[PDB]
Image 1 (cartoon, rainbow over the protein chains, first blue to last red):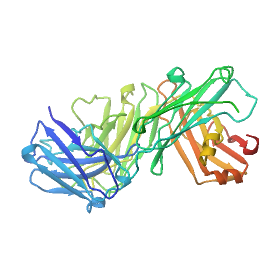
Image 2: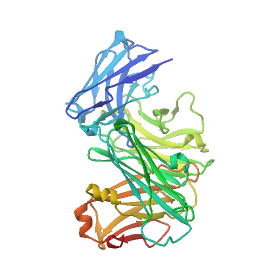
Image 3: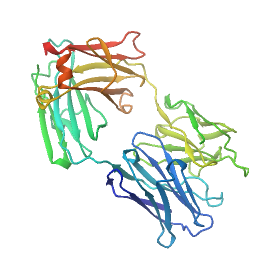
Length: 223
Length: 219
């Protein structure tokens, strides 16, 4: 079959040069009129076309990024490369290598994509999170459900993992996608239980940040 | 550049319904050769986009015929005759006629269900965070429908526009609701300088905001 496989540095710092590779099979860039390109997608956002290179060495670029982009190929190796100079945090994205031919005979459409390579561009250092318990506001109850929370603040890199009662409470739970403040990530999770359950039965936020070897169990204490 | 405008950006449907997604281009995408390089792509979560339709109405091999592409000039439509669960995801239109090649912003095909009011909860800074020298106030707005919601934070009765970060869950696979976390981050100094902290949520399920508050001094 035709396959496209991207590779990249995983993480780099702002100002550095991103060098991506696409290794492919089941077709040749020496075929008239074959082409291969790159499209990226920041997490949670849309698709941005970057560049394309044709069998005859002609190249096409997104004008907005022309001063940072260089696309190239080694047809003998079945490889296409993209260089991006002076990357910054905005160049954090999944980068996909795609085939697109110039004619209808070979397919002038993006039928074949790789699975993509994630590049993180950050000047952040490995940073352990602080883990904070979120107890309901005083005092009574005063209804049939109670909601607790846990705030995981100021970590790098991703991910953190969070469970409640070691997993043994694993519904009534909403754990939210991490967001960037800085620099550093922050994540929250809420758990909702029957009012008679807590504070009488203990509820604990279990958080792990592998990259800093952090493991924290934070019991939610009533006010 | 050619802007590709998709309408709507979120399309709630029930399984078995007909779905229609519009895509408009800001200039013509008839290339100088005869062709209109208008494509539709579907991206399911955790996967690469997949080609559905090219040159306006040509279904790609292996795409089922419940998918159809139509239109003319600057106005295009993707139609699904009966939505299956496997079809849920983000639909992109795209033009390959003019450089830069451009995608629309994406239309998320999602599930309809009955309106549900958010359960709103407010939490003060923890003792731990305060000893550490900071102060975050957290508001959860959980299990609501539709997805559209406004949170505002007030301090001593006055709107606080700065220092707020929000996070949203995808539609729940079991109950088809949405949830949201909002955190107001202050300096410990700012926190200790004011007393009333309010999270209010405006949602179509109420003409009046849902208001959750606390007074720091009573904590």
